[PDB]
Every structure is written in structure tokens, then in C-alpha cells.
Image (spheres, rainbow, N blue to C red):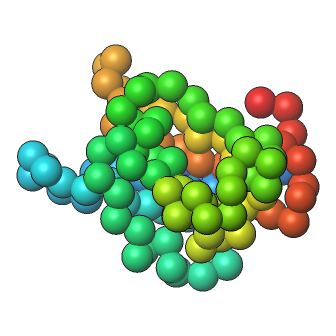
Amino acid sequence: RRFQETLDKIRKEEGYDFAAIAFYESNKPSSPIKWHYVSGNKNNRFKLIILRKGRGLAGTVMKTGKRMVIANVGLALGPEEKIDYPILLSESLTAVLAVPLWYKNQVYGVLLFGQRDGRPLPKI
Ligand SMILES: [Cl-]
């Protein structure tokens, strides 16, 4: 599809190990947010991630409408506090960049880029 092919292209061209897109699961008022599309994923455990608004990497970006950058997960977060950003755990991400996706001044999704094994973030 359009989203999948765009996702694989940007991830490869930007020199990232992983990429994902989160959206609200449904139209329902108390709908959770979930990682819907992935590129460079090691497993399908990202599908176990259920985020309420304001929770996880996707929920935080969705709520604020502001990018989130973690240049070094090991320095920025305690190993125990990683459960608050579950994609970091299922995908063993060591650095992340998460940006809001906008449509007509409204955030509809979260685009995430991640590095593994201590590979630094390329220029943002
Ligand atoms: Cl997450």
C-alpha cells in the first residue's frame, strides 16, 4: 500500500534501522492508539502495544503535537522506565525520533524512526 511503500522508502533513504506509524485503532471516543505500520521490525510484538492518549511514544507526540527525540535511550531512561515507551523494548531501540503527522492542522498519526545497537541518529 501507499503508507507501507512510503514508510520503507523514507526509512531506507534516511539511514534508519526501524520505522513505524501509529494511529487511533477506531472512531470510538476512548479508542486506543496502536502501531499500525512497521518497517525493519524484528518481530510482530509491536501489535501487543495498546496506548491510551498521552501514553507511550505515540500517545505523547499525539497529545502535544511536538516531536520527541531520544539520542541515547540508555542515558535518557532507566532500564525499568522503558515500559512507558514499549516500542523501545519490543524493537530494542537505542535512539529514536518521533514526529507528528498532520492533516489540516490536526495530528492524525505519529511517525517514528529508530536505531538499534548504538547506531547514532542521522541529522534530524
Ligand atoms: Cl510506544
Q: Position of residue 68 (x, y in %)?
A: 60, 35
Residue 26 visible in the displayed image: yes
Above or below for 120 versus 25:
above
* Residue 40 visible in the shown view: no
Q: Nearer the viewer, residue 99 or 118?
A: 118
Tell me how many marks there are.
0
Left or right placement of residue 115 versus residue 119 in this view:
left
Q: Position of residue 83 (x, y in %)?
A: 52, 64
Residue 21 % position (x, y): 49, 52
Name the residue rendered at 68%, 56% in the picture: 78
Q: Residue at x 80, y 63 (%)?
A: 116
* Residue drawn at 89 percent across, 47 percent down: 120
Kindly give the residue lying farthest to the left in the view shown: 28
Q: Nearer the viewer, residue 80 or 51?
A: 80
> Where does residue 32 sit, x and y in percent of width and height?
25, 56
Query: What's the residue at 41%, 27% (across, down)?
Result: 64
Relative height, residue 47 to residue 51 (above, below): below
Quadrant position of residue 94: bottom right
Locate residue 39 relative to residue 110 in the image: left or right: right
93 vs 37, left or right, is right
Q: Quadrant of the C terminus?
A: top right
Hey, which quadrant is residue 93 in on the image?
bottom right
